[PDB]
Length: 246
Ligand SMILES: COc1ccc2ccc(C(=N)N)cc2c1OCC(N)=O
Image (cartoon, rainbow, N blue to C red; front, side, top):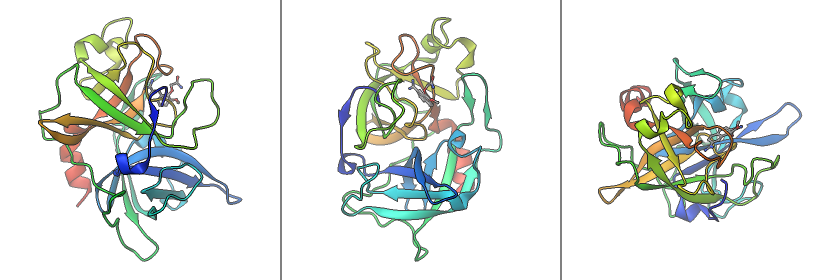
């Protein structure tokens, strides 16, 4: 997250912190994710496509720091890593950039809802918020494009939804951004999601209710002028989510 503010997991209790185990025992942060039901975390396929071995991943719920244990955090393995069969990557655009992670503790249980661990409601079909609506993003991603390390503390920011027509303008992404993608940025281009925030939530308040409107997917640079953050539009994927969670 470029700009924005440091936060803690109690303000984002659906946020999942996903890491990968390496040969030799080192574990590095991969991507964010969101708890949509006690057994299921929703993230982005590009996060896992080059390393699709479910056994390598660790997911945390109720965790506020990158390399520290948060009081009340819960650790899980991935029982099932489901990547979208039609995921593809162009030079910039990532297609069908959605994934599901069935989580389990070492005792074989799913998440236990608490003050710092909660689900995020899925959106309804054909009912996304209008362009101009402010939404929040969360992640452990870079604070500057030039950084090679991630912040130790979780961050959050607020961005505004950009219409498909604006995002398809030639100085923006042209025909590379599709109707299955949602653009969101800062009108002053000072705050954004960045590398490391992929898979994480774009949460919008719709008719007074908090919803997982998007999933961090792709963008040209970070907080660059006319280069919005591009998010997987979750409302298009409700038939796919419902079919793979049962
Ligand atoms: C691999 O790096 C990523 C991966 C995912 C991203 C996702 C979103 C954004 C954004 N500008 N909001 C930037 C991202 C990003 O940085 C853009 C880049 N490397 O040019």
